[PDB]
Amino acid sequence: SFSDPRFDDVKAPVDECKDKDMTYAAPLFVTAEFINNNTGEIKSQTVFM
Amino acid sequence: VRERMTTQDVEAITPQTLINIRPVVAAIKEFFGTSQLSQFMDQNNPLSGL
Amino acid sequence: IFKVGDTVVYPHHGAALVEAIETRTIKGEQKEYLVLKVAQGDLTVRVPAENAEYVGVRDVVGQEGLDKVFQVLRAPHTEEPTNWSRRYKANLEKLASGDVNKVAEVVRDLWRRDQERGLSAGEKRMLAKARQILVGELALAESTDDAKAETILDEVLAA
Image (cartoon, rainbow over all chains, first blue to last red; front, top):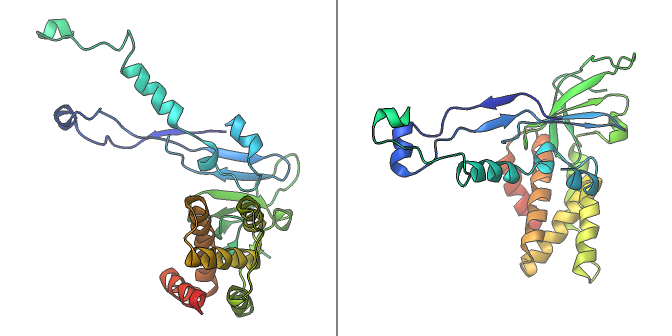
């Protein structure tokens, strides 16, 4: 089960991206949690979406 | 995920293991490039942009 | 037996630092979870202390396990099934068992084989993961100096 999207800063400013032909991006981060039903655990990570 | 979660072994997987983000990033890129709605932004005055 | 500030080995993710004993009760039962994090994938795992040993949490081993896996690491006449896929499935199950002596057997077998031949990318990644978690346990057991544990590991591998 996922949770809580999050944004970092942009990887590059606007004019730099417009020069170097990079797309104006920003990284997602989703706090993904896995549960096991039979034994019972949580697996809280930070998946780069 | 559900193709992967059933197949791989239990108490070895992790959310980094189960998640392939490649369809998500490929889906957003194939929307932004190459869709009939994400248009090449027409500007030859400020008004046409607006 | 688990307390805050302990160092414990969780399979198959190597070393694990406990953080606290989570008192999250659920289904009307005081499920004494314990937040327990690793350093590899930065994942925090909460297992209840009742079935902690049932999932197979395991304390670190001292000098007896140290020279025990040194002896098993030094142990000659390493044999294998001739089919490489049978070999890979065998050491895969041995690595998934999480037993430290099985881990030592796997890394000494794969190091003895690629040290003789130079094996594979799949066997290479196998050796990398197994060596990583064994180095993590040996840095816990010698209580410090993961790089020094790596160097003394490569020392005892040549014997």
